[PDB]
Structures are given as C-alpha cells and as structure tokens.
Length: 70
DNA sequence: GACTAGATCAGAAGCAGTAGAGCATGCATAGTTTT
Image 1 (cartoon, chains in turn purple, brown):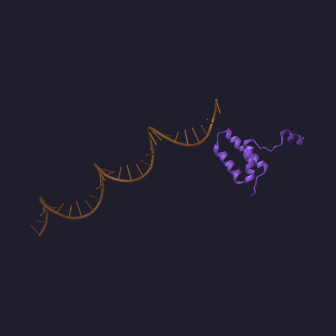
Image 2 (image 1 turned 90 degrees about the vertical axis):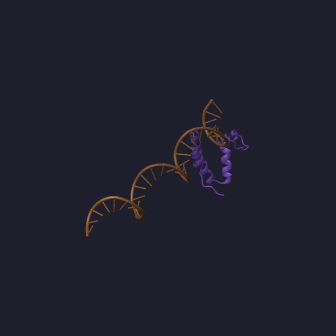
Image 3 (image 1 turned 90 degrees about the horizontal axis):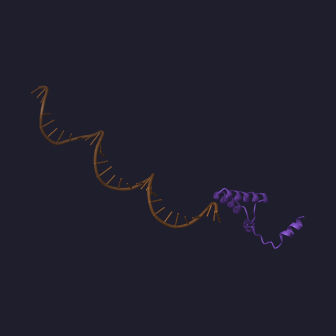
C-alpha cells in the first residue's frame, strides 16, 4: 500500500531499461522491472505502465501544461 | 526492417549393464628326498 521510490530512481530504472534494450540484454530489463514492481504500489504501477506505453490520457492538452509552466 | 521467442531434429555425453581379462588363495595330486 506504500512505495519507497523517488522520481530520480524511477528515471534511472527507465534509463536502464532503454539502454539495455539498445544493447540486447533482456536480463537487465527483467531486473529493473522487478525492482520497480517490488518497490511500488498498484497506483504507481498503473501510472508507470501508462508512462512506458507513452499514453497518460490526462484530458489536459500539452499546450495547457506548457502555458501553466511559463 | 530488425529482432525475439517457441517448437523441433540431430548429435553427443552420461549412465547402466554385460562380457572378458587379470590377480590372489588354496588345495589335489604326484614326485622326490630322507630315514
């Protein structure tokens, strides 16, 4: 019901997944995904799946996010 | 396009079991020597 991951850790794990896919090593992808699964809650994992597939469906336009930012 | 995963065939290594050869133990029998 509670996670123990920070944003930097998640970015590092995703970077490892991408790089190891580029290098044709699936064991490291499995290890990174296992760490993410073991150190995350169900909601966090749902959002991680959405981020991996690259579709969040927030309902707010990218232009709106940029306008809010600056 | 590139790459991965599942299924399948062939060859090879491991293991089990039988056969064949070799090594040690003892004695049967006979021969030879001694009295």
